[PDB]
Image (tube, coloured by chain):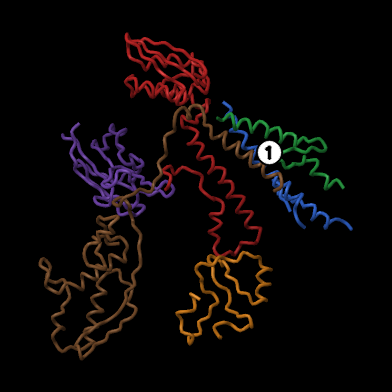
Chain colours: A green, B blue, C brown, D orange, E purple, F red
Amino acid sequence: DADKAVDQIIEDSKRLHIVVNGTGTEQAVAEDGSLLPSVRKALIDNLY
Amino acid sequence: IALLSSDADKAVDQIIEDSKRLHIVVNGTGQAVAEDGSLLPSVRKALIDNLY
Amino acid sequence: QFKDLLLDPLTGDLDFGTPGDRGMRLALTNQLSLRQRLYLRFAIWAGDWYFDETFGFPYRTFVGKKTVKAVLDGRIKSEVRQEPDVLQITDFQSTMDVVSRSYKCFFTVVTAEGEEISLAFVGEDEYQYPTPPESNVQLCGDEGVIINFKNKLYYLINFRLPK
Amino acid sequence: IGAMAANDPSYGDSLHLKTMPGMVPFAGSDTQRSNAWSRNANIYRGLYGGGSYIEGKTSSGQYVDVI
Amino acid sequence: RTVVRTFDFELSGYPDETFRVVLDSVTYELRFMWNERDESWFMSLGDIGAQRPTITSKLTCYSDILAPYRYLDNVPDGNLYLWPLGDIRTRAGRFNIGPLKGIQMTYSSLIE
Amino acid sequence: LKDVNHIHPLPDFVRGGFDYVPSDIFSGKENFEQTLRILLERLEFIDQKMVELAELRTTLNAEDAILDEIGRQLGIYRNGLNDPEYRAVIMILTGNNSKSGTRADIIATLKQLFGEDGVTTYKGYNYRLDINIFNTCMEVTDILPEIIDMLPLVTHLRVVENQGY
């Protein structure tokens, strides 16, 4: 039943990948439904 | 079969600390320490020490 | 740390234990051992135990004779210090009643507690020898390495989203 | 209380450097300790190779053993 | 290989004990050193007044210490073992070595 | 309550020794500490590698570069085997020295190569024996020669391998 863990890992990797490479702005969606900001979104604060 | 994961943890933990530093810097209060030992001020602190 | 059969402080018979755990017990704590070592030392009248004529207390010297309270207290207070693990005696309230001709003293004794040196003769062992693996886990890996990684990923996905 | 109880007041036994079991050392820096000292707020400090009380100063200012 | 028990040892726990013993009518000198990190006794065996010890080994329970060394003219041909008197799971310690302390260090000699 | 294997990295090695500064005389001077820390931290690296020099030499974790040395002492040469299965053959041959080829015994040795439910064995009237494999994790043809060795002198054997039931 490690296939179950491998499943979740598979799309967690994709969520992480989009978050890191979220263009200028991407809104990754977690399983809880909350919204995670790309790094470059998090960088607006300095961007002034 | 997929037990190459024996290398994945050395990156997973590392990204955990990196996220921690990200959080403290962005949401800090009027600091952060990199692996080089140098300091990174949080935005709510950087807004204070700059030239006015 | 002197080991010996435990004597019940309440009745004087061997402490076989409660009805739920009846058995036999050894005196382990230094307090319990010293208690009975003093009790036997004071309860056996001098010379009345065969195989050892020098053991016991000489009550016959005082009982039945006109005696001075001060002399008795010295002997009572001296027999206690024959044990090698007695630190001190705290207080001593010696009182005598002339109407009933009774004598009754109070005092307490202080003793420390030691270590067990070795557990070889008592019950258990303190080591944690390893457990052999199960099935083909050794030659092909283990699934837990996947489960822990999945849990770490899930908890990290949980952390970043504010809650 | 465990350090003063069994001690006759007539001896004038100071409470300066006595050790209090159970307490934990005060971790504040030198500047913080100086601040608290002005407050008459005594601190338990981990000393050179050990840990001990600092001073028996009451809120008014007089040393405790006097009181 | 018939063997008979002929000698027993005791240790006072001092970390650098050294004494002389006689076995099989021959005389040897023994040194015992206590290791902190490994919590084990180190035994050195050699001739009287020898410049260096002939044999050095680590003591363990139920292991034949002299097994690989019965090919020298100055090594006893008997059997040296450590086995416990109490629970079988107890391992050799510092103060638990002796005829009644828990571990019985013993030497036995073949019948010739 | 305690591990019997005392060979472990010393816990908190660095803060020890610093504990031997007499009365905090130098502490907080930031000039003596760095000099002492720089020297002590070198022992940290050496202390750590003392373990792998013993840990990595065990047959369970030995890498192929040195596993050959372990096999060489036992006469089991690499031949064309690769690391993951070369470990297996070493275990199989060594384990054969205390065996009797009984039905219960044979199941035990196959147990270490195919998990719990990955193997089953049918038996036949005239010396026939059968081996079934369900969850092989290594290529079996190179392991086959040993699988014959731990069987009685007169066994008649069939080998069939498949994935799953």
Residue neighbourhood size for the residue with mark 1, other residues' Cα within 10 Å, grouped as few (<14), some (14–19), many (≥20) = few
Task: Estimate the x, y position of residue F13 in percent, counting from the top left.
Answer: 54, 50
- Report whether F63 appears left or right of E48: right
Q: Residue tagged by mark 1?
A: A31
Q: Is the residue D43 above or below the residue F131 in the image?
A: below
Task: Estimate the x, y position of residue E44 in percent, counting from the top left.
Answer: 34, 43
- Report whether F43 appears left or right of C111: right
Task: Estimate the x, y position of residue E62 in percent, counting from the top left.
Answer: 30, 39
Foreground pick, E102 / F44:
E102
Total numbered labels: 1
Q: Regarding mark 1 in the picture, which secondary structure is present there?
A: loop
Task: Estimate the x, y position of residue F52 in percent, counting from the top left.
Answer: 51, 37
Chain for numbered disc 1: A
Q: In which quadrant of the rendered image does the N terminus of chain C lie?
A: bottom left
Q: Quadrant of residue C159?
A: top right
Q: Which residue lies furthest to the bottom in this view?
A: C99
- Report whether B12 appears left or right of F47: right
Q: Which residue lies furthest to the right in this view?
A: B52
Q: Residue furthest left?
A: C50
At horizontal 24% and vertical 64% (from top left) the residue drawn is C7
- Report whether F109 appears left or right of A15: left
Foreground pick, F101 / C1:
F101
User: Label 1 is placed on what type of residue?
Assistant: Glu
At horizontal 79% and vertical 44% (from top left) the residue drawn is A42
At horizontal 32% and vertical 12% (from top left) the residue drawn is F153
At horizontal 44% and vertical 16% (from top left) the residue drawn is F132
Q: Is the residue C117 above or below the residue E80 in the image?
A: below
